[PDB]
Image (cartoon, rainbow over all chains, first blue to last red):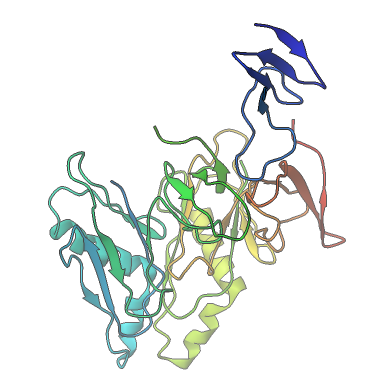
Length: 49
Length: 149
Length: 149
């Protein structure tokens, strides 16, 4: 439904979800390595209502 | 479908047995070590080529190659491995049956030819997921790559 | 374009094979070990100079030097390596094919002459990027330097 920027992260809204991208790179919704989670990974926070 | 048997060199009289698919494929006994010419037979590549010759004669299609430090048992697009064990003869550190599922980053085979994948699982020491690592032959590294399917 | 083959000394009868560019360059068999004068042939520098003599005779231009603990295979500004493997004969710890791409800081060659670069990649243990490290010959260190191009 929307494009929004938030702390270097491109972001989309969704059915109920908020999906922010990677910190340095806008067009990337996946972490660099699922070994060693590295604090810049994309986040999937469902709006809990 | 694929598989690797590492070889690391003998040590003066043990049995080297490679079970593929249930049968007792590829037996060899390192000699007694009494005569001085038997020190040639603990060479890793000589042992690899003898194990691969036994492997080719005792399996039907099963294309295997003598690598730098392995033999690369492949199944010919039909049947699978379905059972893969290796009676070392010495302790665990003589010949290693290694597959696509090593359980740490330290236990990981030395050459493992160019297109090869390992699902690193666990080690139960850090709260970590299970990540996949591919080898490269031009640059001898182990970088992380995708899943299979 | 460059390359290094470390040598670490023999161990009484194995094959030492250095593949450059696909061909089977530079074969040598360490002797049986029966006669007492064959202990000279597990010297690392004697083995290095014999492997380099084989290397110079079995390649065309290919300037190689016998270092402290290596031989330094160079390509003469035209063609490249394109394939670089080394059948150890013993386990991984006899002669090491090492390139510009070692995968940790621990695995890193001992001398590696003065102008040399290594892209340290991964090790998949810490969330770390990939950094480059240069050797110095006056002060035997490994400090970090730039990228190549």
